[PDB]
Amino acid sequence: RDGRDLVLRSGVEETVEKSVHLAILYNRVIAQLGLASFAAGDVIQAYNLLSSLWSNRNHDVLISQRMPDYVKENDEEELKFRDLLVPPHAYIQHAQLELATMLSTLVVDTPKEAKKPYEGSRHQSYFFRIINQMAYQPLLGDPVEFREQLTAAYINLKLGDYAKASEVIKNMGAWSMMPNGDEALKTFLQHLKEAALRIFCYNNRCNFATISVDLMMKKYGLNENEVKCIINDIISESNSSLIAFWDREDKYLHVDRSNTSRLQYLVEGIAESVVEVAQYSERRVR
Amino acid sequence: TLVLPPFVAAAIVEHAKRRRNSAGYLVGSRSGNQITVTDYIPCTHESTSDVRTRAYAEELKERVALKKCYTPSITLVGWYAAATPEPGKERAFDLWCQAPGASFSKIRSHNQAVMLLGRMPTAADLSIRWEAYITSNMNDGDSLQCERMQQLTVCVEAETPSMNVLLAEMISKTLYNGSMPYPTNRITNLDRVAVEAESREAEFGRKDNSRNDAEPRPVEAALLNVQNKLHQAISHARAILVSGNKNKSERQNESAAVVENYEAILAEKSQQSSRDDFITESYKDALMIKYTAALLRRHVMEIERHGR
Amino acid sequence: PMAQRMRISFSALTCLGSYAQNATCHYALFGRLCGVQLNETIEVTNVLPPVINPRPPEDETPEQREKRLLAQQREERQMYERMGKMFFKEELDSYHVGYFAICSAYTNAPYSVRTVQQLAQLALDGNPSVLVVYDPFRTSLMGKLYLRAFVPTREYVEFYTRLTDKRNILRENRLMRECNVGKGGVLREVKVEVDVDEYQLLCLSGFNVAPLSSTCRTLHSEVMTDYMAALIESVRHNADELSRGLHSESYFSQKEESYGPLGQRIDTLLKLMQLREQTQHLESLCDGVLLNTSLLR
Amino acid sequence: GRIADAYVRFFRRFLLSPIPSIVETDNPHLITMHKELEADREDFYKEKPNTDRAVRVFCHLLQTLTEMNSWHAAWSTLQCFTRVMQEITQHPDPSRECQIIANSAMAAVFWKCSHYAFHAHCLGVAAFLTGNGGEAAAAASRAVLATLCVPNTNKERRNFERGSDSVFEKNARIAQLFGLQSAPAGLALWQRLQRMQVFQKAFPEVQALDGLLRNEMSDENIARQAIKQLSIIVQKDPSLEMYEKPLRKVVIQRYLECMAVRTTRVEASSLQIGENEASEEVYIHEIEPYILNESGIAVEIDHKTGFISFSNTTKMRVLEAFDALAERVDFHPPALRRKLDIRPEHLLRAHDRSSIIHRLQHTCEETAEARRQSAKEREEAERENARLER
């Protein structure tokens, strides 16, 4: 909070444009702020700060290390990107930033279904994944690795449930690396519960959910909560396609969606009508 | 078992004719116990005078064909020839014997050919118009290789083409016909009958009429109204304490079953579930868009008229 | 001219199957229609394709040109192997009677106007060549399975002496355009299924007896019972294709805050046809769904 | 992996020499190098040990154990291994032994990954070639896996479709080496097993187990318990025990299919919970999610007042349609029959007219006219070209 407040107040974002040492500093502080936001334990501002730093450029010499292309083979011009700056004994940890970025993206972006705005993902890695390393192929499986843990976690988080996603994450191979603790893990775990519940409803053919009552807390899958404040906020709505006649007394949801596919069909017919209407408006001017 | 598409067969009737005698080379591929002859092409050979074999001729033809292709899913499989199928005979048999051996060209994977004899004239007294054979013994050199023939049955595809030809034939009770717009819908009792009526209706002239139709709309309406009234009559005929003999027995049992099924569906339906009503609503959506399409056509027609 | 009454042995997929062997789906003009004059009619017996693909990633000079040259040579060889025999005595087959596009979303304006009608229908009088567009199973079974046969328009010295222009404020442009359109061909039509081939005979002889007829009967019954599954496949996808086609029409004619350039007057592609086709497919769907639920009522 | 894979590839598998390219260019001694290489490849096929095959099988097993793919080099090994495994060239005795060694190596690794259609193929290939004794017992057991998986291709989960298509395309590609061109499944897997000795042999108990797993069964839980007992012991195989985890899953999916089919809809849940097997063994904590997540087909599964509703299949409507169809006035059986008769009658008439039999004259007349017309058209085209050219 304090770092973000000071940078935005002091108006120091137009002195980093020219003066090249200050730029690297600028990148260094933006990265650190996004890491700190992640690691005491919310997704946003952490997603916003960190995504902005990334994605783009490749190309990252910009805090550390690394040299661009190309450099260092050529020639005597090495000494520009090896003197702007980079400073030593810092960086701050590579890896840690990457975990923060990918995890932040996963919580935000997966809930941007309704269903079917289908969706060009907003990260450099994420868009790549389907063509790249998820794909449909590599040979043939088979997590757990390393980074394909994150891919496995994304598959589990989408559907299903939750439990599998937690198992890959908590555990194994990835987390323990944060020096800002267990605290960050607990916050992130709660965020995973919230967004796993959010995605899980949509979905469920074509609904029903709260199956049952008490089980809904229990399996989705942390005990036993606010209960009502968490469950109501996640379900609610009403925006977009309808859910609910929700009866909170018996804790039963009587969706009556009417309907998934028919809504889309009507949307296509509306879309076609607006083009034709506009086309014919121009013709009556002419 | 020789698999032939049916465009192939029509082509063979054209190629069999008109000129005396014609022959050609047949191509395709093979899979296991089936040989798929998928195409062919002709050549100028006289099969009743030992022309142009040799087996220089076979080699030359093969090279030319290969050049024309390359795809390995049309490879040379064998020869087609206009008649003789054993009066006669010997000339056709002789051409075959000559062809393998001097050359040994080309495309094989077993010592082979396939022979299709086409009857040149249209005959059916005892004649079989396309006859299929596959070499057996198969001496692999005897002078230039000789043969005896195992008869193979001719058969057709696979999926859509064969079915399409058959369906087209079936239609004919009025018209003889493609598959064309407007029709068909095909869930029968009722749709098929409607389609038949439509076909009869369509063409009389494209039109000696203004105002209003009485042809298909009362044929469809009559069939539906007859079905309703008839079903009521049959059920009523049961409804006098008889389950046996009245209609033969037999109508009554069917009607009773229909009543029970509809009632059961209705009871289950509302409310968990609505489903046939929702299907009716998606029909209304479709109908609304059909109205919109008609309206778009009318708007375009006004602009078209005002711009011509 | 050499296009008067077209005899089609189609239902056995005379040319469509020949194309299908060389693959499909495809999205552009793909070849020539071959056939020959016989008794009363021209029977369209055969099709052959030149194949041009320029290596789309990444071009840069000469490969596109090379491919076109190669394609022409390949085409000549293919044509010759059928043509040559004909020349020598008779055989058959000869003789260019059309061009063909395989299963494209719609045939747009430069395919007809600039790849056919540009100078190859001003070098031909009476238009003996007919441009055929096929969209069958890819737009759903029935009501689509035949066929567009177009007589491609255009004689074309009334807006070509110099040179080709449009406004932006139509009136002058249109008048010339109308004259060009008239000769032709707007979309206009060629007779189909009005002949008895007598070459159908081998297919008629087949089969019957026995696995064919038996399988077909069983299949027909199964379809008649069914109707559930293919509803999903049809209906939604058609709306998407229609929307995609129409929103192109809108861009084309309403362009975009201003004016024409319109067609100037409209159309040599498929706009009017698509609106009619949309009405007919929807009517067929509505009647079948209606009948299903009336039988349950 | 890479280095080694290249080594074999460079060696016999595919050669060209490489290099030469004859002449001698300008550099001597090329002949000696070429000769040595030729001699070595020749020596390999077959001088009788392939300890090579054993080492290659060993390494690939280790390779997928490790962690377990990445972009890795497991795939490149398998493509190289498939190339090597086309021993041909020489035959049969040594080559056959190598093949048995080879095709076990492959099939096992599939299980570790996912996967299991390729496993089913490779085990049936393995069982074709060996099957006396120890080998026979192993082959017989592996049967269970083949039956167990692969009764479906594609499918699930919406959003998703593009991914499914891509996966299918990839499966087809793997297929190629390997030696089909599409992924193996279903009926064909069963059919090839019946044609050989490899389901016949086999053991009776395993065949009967397959029997239970592949047809419709009911009461389900009793059957499931029997299946479990057989897996644990009979035929005293450890392969069965390790297969038991998908097997346990799969019987539920079969039960769900049977219930939907028979049976317009049913109140399922309690029976399923029970089936998993008694009590102090359930919390529906995880048992009910396993039931909800499982389904081989898109259906409703979803209720919260207890039990499960389905809304498919709609058997009653189909039955109603048939009853209605039958009578009716009569109408459909007579109509159908008349049409059926009509197509042969018409066909016969047309055929006869063309032939001899009603006419003969018509065909001849048409042919004569046709020849004249064809000639004229051809001539016109020829004349036009000639005139233009000159």
Image: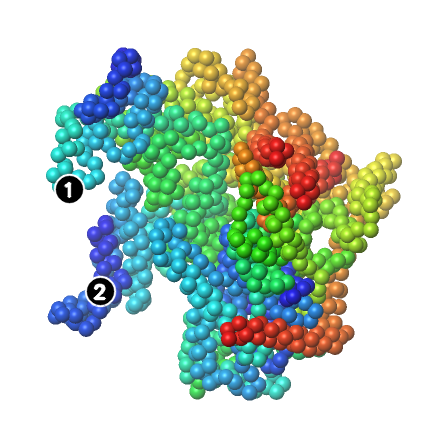
Of tags 2 and 1, the one toward the viewer is 1
Asked whether, in this view, residue C7 is left or right of residue D193, the answer is right
Image location of residue C83, percent across then percent down: 53, 72
**Mark 2 falls on what kind of element?**
loop
Q: Quadrant of residue A277?
A: top right
Residue type indicated by callout 2:
Pro
Could you tell me which secondary element the residue under label 1 belongs to? Answer: loop
Disc ID at residue B35: none
Q: Relative to the observer, which residue lies in front, C156 or B281?
A: C156
Amino acid beneath label 1: Asn
**Which chain does the numbered disc 2 sit on?**
D
The quadrant in which residue A149 appears is top left
Q: Is residue C276 above or below residue A31?
A: below
Judge if badges 2 and 1 mark residues of a common chain: no
Quarter placement of the C terminus of chain A: top right
Which residue in the protein does label 2 denote? Answer: D18
